[PDB]
Length: 284
Length: 284
Ligand SMILES: NC(=O)c1ccc[n+]([C@@H]2O[C@H](COP(=O)([O-])OP(=O)(O)OC[C@H]3O[C@@H](n4cnc5c(N)ncnc54)[C@H](OP(=O)(O)O)[C@@H]3O)[C@@H](O)[C@H]2O)c1
Ligand SMILES: NC(=O)c1ccc[n+]([C@@H]2O[C@H](COP(=O)([O-])OP(=O)(O)OC[C@H]3O[C@@H](n4cnc5c(N)ncnc54)[C@H](OP(=O)(O)O)[C@@H]3O)[C@@H](O)[C@H]2O)c1
Ligand SMILES: C[C@]12CC[C@@H]3c4ccc(O)cc4CC[C@H]3[C@@H]1C[C@H](Cc1cccc(C(N)=O)c1)[C@@H]2O
Ligand SMILES: C[C@]12CC[C@@H]3c4ccc(O)cc4CC[C@H]3[C@@H]1C[C@H](Cc1cccc(C(N)=O)c1)[C@@H]2O
Image (tube, rainbow over all chains, first blue to last red; front, side):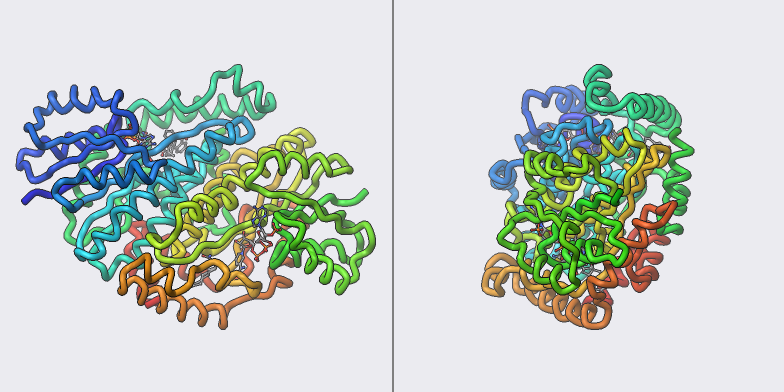
């Protein structure tokens, strides 16, 4: 009788807060499969489930590495109810630093998890939704998928890629009754903002002094933007529930309107000149 | 004394026509390293060089697989003049079909060549430009990097990714005196439009009947768009030369204005609803 939800990337942040928001819903409408790359990281998902008092049987954890199509197929197999009514593609990696300072493996990894991983989910789960003629897909997006940010070149590349992927799919899926939406997040208060950049010694080793200095300047500024604009994952989760509930969902939901001016400026000078000038000024 | 140009992907199409346009320039200002994945494919680059009568010493071929950072490093080593004044990132793969019908290897390949490959070029060549405080980078872009097209989900993902990569980099590079521009191509008359989709038997095997039917409909329409809008690589090459010559280059050049309305519609409804509705109507 329940809405079956499968979420990727639940060990922390938005995926964690969404899974237990859904599982602990006063109305008990949702059966949640919360998936994680590594089950050793599953504790917080249980600390928090106990805190919001999720009913027994509301929340099931599954191991699911989105780099591995056999792992995607094994997690699907484990969906006893034999359908997924809501698929949430949220697993993601960050990467921050001078481009020439990033390892080639890390670059490939970010693309594999953020982009190919989402493809793998969609390949494995869309066919059955198209046949039932129903289903909702919610993809965690970013404002860095809508505008480019210095030192986030690869991260932005992976989030722009998701815009292209999802927008392309949406044009097709429209008459199938399968709804795909991006939830476009600005800065969110989670953990992310030191885990994903090397040591100062490492970075200086791999770039010039002037680039290093501009990286410090970007970081300082980034910290201020987070301090003034970062939303909690509670607020973010609730936008996913809005999309999930809309009878006619749009391709994009924004968790904040704050960056929509910047976006408009981007969008009305397609030479990119005004955007690049404005953002250079703003960051540096 | 000459402008040193290194171009990736020269065996056919834009990269081929650009390399020999530059090499055969009446003024002889340009020394061209034309790179190819496979030297067995280098003949047309010589048939055409003979046709436009390129001087001896204008055009040098090099083997360069952008999937392989050792290959990138070997091609760089071979740049006798010890600098590159113009780097042209043009190597690219296409991929066309229902998403669930695309092999996981082909998906990874398109991202590796189109996105990671361009990163590898930039990692290998930008550092020296930043130090000299000069250099031009020209990246072949696509209108499918600015708007999503059904059945081009992965292709579009890879071209959106390039927008994110290049835009991010441009915000940083502005005060370095290194200029990065995307050349945004609509349909171009080359070879591409059958090489990159499976047999009808293969595709039907891998999708539903309704998706298959919509794929036929998209293809029919695509053929009409090409028949009415496709530009020759001569026209396209000349936009690269425009960018190369501009004293103050912008982030984007468009080879046609034709899709700029469609783009504006995209850009002024950030819910994506108007775009997805318009494009669904237009394609189907
Ligand atoms: N953090 C922010 O400031 C912020 C801002 C805007 C948008 N977002 C977006 O939200 C998403 C997640 O960010 P978040 O920290 O807020 O939430 P999140 O739910 O923690 O997502 C990041 C997650 O990716 C998962 N992951 C990493 N590698 C994986 C793999 N190989 N396979 C499967 N999952 C993997 C991790 O846990 P598992 O063990 O579960 O897999 C981790 O939970 C991203 O797509 C990002 O765009 C975040
Ligand atoms: N064709 C169109 O209709 C059209 C339209 C809009 C934009 N464009 C853009 O222009 C670019 C090329 O298209 P084109 O056919 O017109 O010109 P192109 O110069 O032929 O580019 C495609 C090329 O990629 C190269 N390539 C493939 N795999 C490679 C690898 N592993 N390493 C290095 N190079 C590899 C191929 O030759 P090599 O042997 O040289 O490597 C091939 O020449 C793309 O980035 C595309 O966005 C084309
Ligand atoms: C792009 C962004 C919205 C725009 C923000 C902005 C706006 C204006 C401005 O002037 C500066 C800034 C800097 C911060 C920017 C946010 C970064 C954040 C995404 C994020 C989070 C964690 C790790 C990574 C990574 N690994 O790369 C990336 C969010 O999506
Ligand atoms: C995206 C596009 C501009 C917009 C065009 C359009 C506009 C309006 C419309 O209604 C239909 C269409 C269909 C054709 C569209 C072009 C495709 C082309 C890129 C390309 C070339 C060769 C192979 C692939 C691949 N492997 O995926 C991709 C060019 O970049």
